[PDB]
Structures are given as C-alpha cells and as structure tokens.
Image (cartoon, coloured by chain):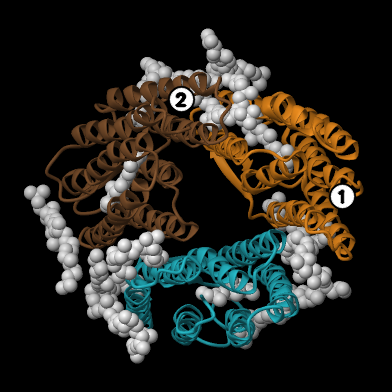
Chain colours: A cyan, B orange, C brown
Amino acid sequence: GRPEWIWLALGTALMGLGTLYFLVKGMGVSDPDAKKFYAITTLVPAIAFTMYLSMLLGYGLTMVPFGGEQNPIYWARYADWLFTTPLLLLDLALLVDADQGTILALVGADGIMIGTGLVGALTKVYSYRFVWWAISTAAMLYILYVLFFGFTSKAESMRPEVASTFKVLRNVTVVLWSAYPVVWLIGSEGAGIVPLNIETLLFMVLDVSAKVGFGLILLRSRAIF
Amino acid sequence: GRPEWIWLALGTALMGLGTLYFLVKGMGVSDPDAKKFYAITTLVPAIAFTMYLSMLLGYGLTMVPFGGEQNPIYWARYADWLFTTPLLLLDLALLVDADQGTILALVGADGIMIGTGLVGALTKVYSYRFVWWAISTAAMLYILYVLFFGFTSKAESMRPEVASTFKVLRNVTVVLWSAYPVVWLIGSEGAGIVPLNIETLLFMVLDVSAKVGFGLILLRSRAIF
Amino acid sequence: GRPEWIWLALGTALMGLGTLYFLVKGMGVSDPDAKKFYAITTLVPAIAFTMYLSMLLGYGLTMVPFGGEQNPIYWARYADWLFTTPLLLLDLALLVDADQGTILALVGADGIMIGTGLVGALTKVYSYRFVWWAISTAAMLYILYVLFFGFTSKAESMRPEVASTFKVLRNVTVVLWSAYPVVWLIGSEGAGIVPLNIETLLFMVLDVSAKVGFGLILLRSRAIF
Ligand SMILES: *C\C=C(C)/C=C/C=C(C)/C=C/C1=C(C)CCCC1(C)C
Ligand SMILES: *C\C=C(C)/C=C/C=C(C)/C=C/C1=C(C)CCCC1(C)C
Ligand SMILES: *C\C=C(C)/C=C/C=C(C)/C=C/C1=C(C)CCCC1(C)C
C-alpha cells in the first residue's frame, strides 16, 4: 500500500477533527439523554481515528493470497466497523426508543455482518470469499429492514423533532450502509473491477459520511434532548 | 481435515435450518418478553451456522504442533462457543429472572471457560494443554452450580409453566455442557483416545442439541411469555 | 523470557489467592448491591490469574522486531487489561452511581486506551510505537479526569461511608493507573531504559495492587452495601 496513503491520511485527519468537534461540542451538555447521544456519537469517530491511523502507519494492512496474487487487505476496516456500526445502531435505537429485544437482534446481526465480512476478506479461496459476502449482505438487509420498517413506526409515536431527525438519519444509513457490499464486491477484496486506490477512496468517503456526517446531522439537532 | 467434512457440512445444514425455523416462528410474536427470548435464541444458531461453515470451507481449521505432530485444531469451535454460551446463559437467566450480579458472574465465568479452553487447544506444550483444561472445567463446574442450585430456587418463585420449563432446560444444559470437557479430553485436542472424525461427530451432536434442541424446548413453550 | 519467570509465577500465585479470598469472602453476602460489587471485583483477579499463567507457561509471550532486535513482548498483559480495567471502572461507577452515558464514555475510552496501547507494543516500526503510546495516554488522562472531577462530585451526594471509600479508591486508581504509561515508556516496549526483568517486576506490583489491593480496600468496606 502506497498510492492510497493520501486517502488514509485524509481519513485520519477528518475522523480526528470529527472527534475534537463533538467532544468540544458536547462539553456544555447537561441533559442525560443528550449526554448519552454525545457519548455514543463521539466514540464512533474516535475509534475510526485509531483504525485509520493504523492503516496509514502500516499496521492495519495485511496480505492475503487469493488468485495468482498476494492481495493487500486493510483489516483495520473490519476492526473499525465492528465497534462502530453497533454504536451507530444504538444512536438510532435510543432516538426511536427501541426494545431491548430488537437491539440485541440488531447488534447480534451486525456483529455477524462484520465478522462474516471479515472472514470473506481473509479467505484464501477466491470463490468462497463470495459466499461470506452473501451471508454478510443478507444480514445487512435484515438490519436495514427493521431499521426502516420497525424503527420508523417506533419514531412516529414521538415528538416530531425526533420523528423527523430519525427520518433523515434512517435514509442516510440505509443508503450509505448498502454502499459497502457494493464497493467491496467491485474492489480488490472481491470481483476486482476497481483498483485499491479507488476502493480506499470510496470507503473513505462512506466512513467519513457515516461516522462524522451522521454525527453532525444528529448532534446538531434538538432531537437528542 | 477431510473425513469429518460430512459432520461439519451436516452441522452447517442443521444450524442453518435451525435459524430459519426460529426466525419464521418468532415472526408473529408481539410479547416483548417472548420477543427477547426469540431474539436471544435465534442468534445462537445463526452464529453457530457461520462458525460451522468456516470449518467446512476450511477457514476455522488450524494446525497446532504438540507431541511429535502438527495437530488439526478447529478453533471456530471456540469462536462459536464464546458468543453462543453467554446467550444461552441469558435465556436461562431471563427465564428465571436473575440478578444483574449473578449474570455478570456467569458471563464472566463463561468467557473464562471458553478463552481458557481455547488457550488449551492452541498450547504447543502437550502437558500444559491439560492445566487449561482443568481451569476451563473448574469454571464450568462453577457455572453449572449456580445454574442448578441458584437458578432453580429462583424459578420456584414463578409461574409453574416457567418453573417447569426451566427444570427441563436446566437438566439439558447441565448434562450437555459437561460432555464437552469429556469429549475434548479424549479427542485429538487432549489425551488422544478418539480420532478427529469422531471428536467432530460428537461435538456436532452436542452443538446441535445445545443450540437447536434447547431452542426448540424453550421457544415451543409458553414459559417465554 | 526466563529471568522474570519468578515475577510471573509470583503474580500467578497472588492473583490466584486473590480470587480465592474474594470468592470465599462474598459467599455469605445477601445484599444485591454488595453481591454485584463482589461479582465485578472477584472477576478482575480471576482473569488476571489466567493471563499471568499464560505468561508463565509461555503462551502470553510474543516476539516483535523493532530496532536491530526481536523483542519479547508479553501481550497477555494487554488481553488482561482489556477486560480488567473496564470492570474496575464499573466498580467505581456503581459506587458513585454514574450515568449510563458517562460509563459508556469511560468504557469506550478505556477500550481505546488498551487496544491502542496494544497496537503500540506490536508495532514493528520503533518510532511509531510512540505515537500509539501518546494516543493511549491521552485517553487515560481523559479517564482519570472524569474519574477524579466527575465521579468525586457524584460521590459527594452519597452516604459518607461511600463518599470516603470512593475517595480512597479514586486516589488509588489515579496514582496506580498513571504508572503504566511511565513503566511502559522506560521498559523494553518503549525507550529501553529498564530491562525486561524489572519492567515485568514493576507491572507485577501495579497489577497486584490495582487488582487485588483495590479489591481489598473496596470489599472490606461497608460502602459496597
Ligand atoms: C462505519 C460505518 C458504517 C455504517 C459501516 C458499515 C459497514 C458495512 C455495512 C459493511 C457491509 C459489508 C457487507 C454488507 C458485505 C461485505 C463486507 C462488508 C463488511 C463490506
Ligand atoms: C454451543 C453450546 C454449548 C453449551 C457449548 C459449551 C461448551 C463448553 C461448555 C466447553 C467446555 C470446555 C471445557 C469445560 C474444558 C475444555 C475446553 C471446552 C471449551 C471444550
Ligand atoms: C490491571 C489494572 C489496571 C488499572 C491496568 C491499567 C493499565 C493501563 C492504565 C495501561 C496504560 C497504558 C498507557 C496509558 C499507554 C501505554 C500502554 C499502556 C497499556 C501500558
């Protein structure tokens, strides 16, 4: 890895600045609900920072042999999404006021979506790498389903400021989230159609949007109170 | 690994079907307690599926050198039991209505039972592999103890449908769970007395029973409401 | 690793005895709050035991090449602190009666402090190992901050036996905790100024104090009721 260094260093900067902003922002917050939202939201980019730094400094990169090649796989991406997506799922669940049962379904389904997708990236048998991608995406579909059809109805029985803020975020996650299994598939980890430099650029845009952008939408609203 | 492939492929099928059944089953459930039970219970085999698939497709298998040999160790078994046994512990705890303190003891003890048992499997010094087995089983004994003597009394102060369903499950876990440290010890991971093909068959029967069977007993009862 | 074996074997003994004491001690406890305190507190050394044993028996030791050398890094230390420090953070939070938001901040910050510090230990580029140490310590400072200025005020609105016991423990963690990034820096994992034998002795004293000592202070008080 070298050409994409710029993308990784750029993602390390943004996530870093993204954490600083939220920390400084939530400093004056007294409301225990809002205070929880800033807690969950600030932690997402903080983790993303460390994981992006590990990729830039070289750590988060590995080499997996599939096909007639040793392929550079950035695993820190999976280590990032493992703790990051569940927290993003909690923001949405606190907002909408979800059941302890549905949250456990989602966190349980999310862990499977990431780990299973990680197994795909490390799989040395090219073909197989696609089975796990299939299992990983099936689980994402299940998540975006209850997040769209379950949470929405759940947000409707709440204050309009909350109801709407959720609508924005709902669309934002459904659209962003479903980009990963598409970027992955065409990127170097799957059916190579796009080079690593681009794949890395693409994931960099989704990560910043999903982690920092989502945070802005949410934290800068009154829906968190 | 090859001869046992049939056992792994059979366990991948059952766990897979086991997840589909519970998902489709709990679909009509409205009760937030039952809905939590289906949440916890459905997730157990789902994880088991992925872990069993990883073993079949080759991933979940490693080679550990102990003795005058490089020994095939299926680690995905430990990765499975790590998230699976705590969830099974939560089903029993929700049912019986346990204290947040005892649950933390059990989950804390369970994590130690699996990780410690994993350390045993990966230990390159043959002798040592038995110390960890001893520490892993001591922790299982501690778990089956409060699960038998602590939870039972706890179930007694509840509706008889719940009290009884717990009794069934209680026996089912105490008996099933204590089979693992026995199968392990005689299997290839320990004092080789049984071949890998059998060890794998045995764990396959315990896993299906513990994950799917237990689920059936529980989900098909009214005790979950 | 060999000369320090005595330190590791001594830490394995103490942690082991430390677990036995608390188990036997909390056996008569009926109070659900105290029962939670013994639950959280007993589990800290139990984990520490297994991790210290893994280091003695050889498992928890790795070799990382940085500089003109292959350096012996005991990673089981990080695997220990990963589950151990969050639990110690929960003791303090239950005692003081903290918000679910602040606890998530602390556990989230703590995980980053350990993992980030682990990345440092495994980093093959000598220089970099210091960036992660910096990120790991920044996160510890953030933790000792709210643990000192946030929790204290929180303890003040409680029974004096609790208020005071917290004061003792507060100082004990702030002082002990800030010794690790200092021992690390001068030890073999960082700017080698002290040999492994000493580094290991030092961490052995902090671990016993933080895990067992802290437990004694806390469990032998009435503040846990
Ligand atoms: C960092 C924030 C978010 C929302 C990241 C989400 C990541 C995913 C939803 C990943 C999805 C994947 C799928 C569906 C299948 C292939 C493997 C992936 C992990 C890339
Ligand atoms: C998947 C469901 C269950 C109930 C699996 C449980 C697994 C165990 C109880 C494992 C026990 C072990 C012991 C006691 C000691 C050796 C190592 C094992 C992990 C096999
Ligand atoms: C086992 C109990 C405690 C309190 C252990 C705590 C460990 C730390 C606070 C570690 C701190 C580190 C820092 C701050 C930076 C370098 C890496 C360390 C993990 C050693």
State the image coordinates of residue B73 (x, y, percent, origin top left). Answer: 62, 41
Using the image as rendered, state which of residue B71 and residue C214 is in the foreground. C214
State the image coordinates of residue A201 (x, y, percent, origin top left). Answer: 45, 86
Horizontal side of residue B169 vs B154, given as left or right: right
Horizontal side of residue B222 vs A61, given as left or right: right
Q: Which residue is mark 2?
A: C19
Please say if C51 is above or below A103. above
**Other-residue count near label 2 (Cα within 10 Å), few / some / many at <14 / 14–19 / ≥20:** many
Chain ID for label 1?
B
Q: Which residue is painted at 28% across and 36% down in the image?
A: C168
Horizontal side of residue A24 vs B105, given as left or right: left
Q: Which amino acid type is shown beneath numbered disc 1?
A: Leu
What secondary structure is marked by label 1?
A: helix
Q: Which residue is mark 1?
A: B219
Chain ID for label 2?
C
State the image coordinates of residue C11 (x, y, percent, origin top left). Answer: 34, 26
Please say if C21 is above or below A99. above
Q: Which residue is painted at 26% across and 28% down in the image?
A: C4
Q: Quadrant of residue A185?
A: bottom right
State the image coordinates of residue C14 (x, y, percent, origin top left). Answer: 36, 22
**Residue C64 seen in the current view:** no
Q: Which amino acid type is shown beneath numbered disc 2?
A: Thr
Query: Dividing the image into 4 quarters, which one contains the N terminus of chain A?
Result: bottom left
